[PDB]
Amino acid sequence: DKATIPSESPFAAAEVADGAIVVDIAKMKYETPELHVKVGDTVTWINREAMPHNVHFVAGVLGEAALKGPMMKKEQAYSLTFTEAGTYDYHCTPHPFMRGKVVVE
Ligand SMILES: [Cu+]
Image 1 (cartoon, rainbow, N blue to C red):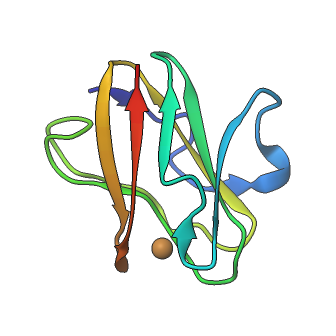
Image 2: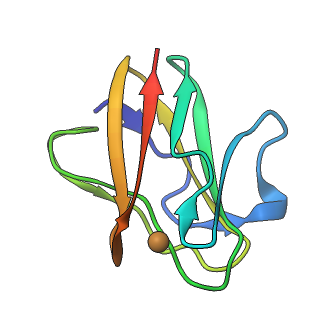
């Protein structure tokens, strides 16, 4: 695939790695809707609000299957490490008007 998953389960915001590249989620939006990172970088999303959110990449984007991330509760986090250059669109499964992309350069 074009991403690896450090933790299949969400984890606490306080447990996010020191060097972390963070996208906050609040007010029903991804706070950085267009993020540029390098090959090999790990992106971490953190839900800052009570409404559960996830990130969802449809089939063919990060790999052959869809990657439907777990639902993050308030102050939970989820990471993906990107291993190939490209542009990767994602949305929130229950709220598909929430859209973002990671541009890996
Ligand atoms: Cu959401």
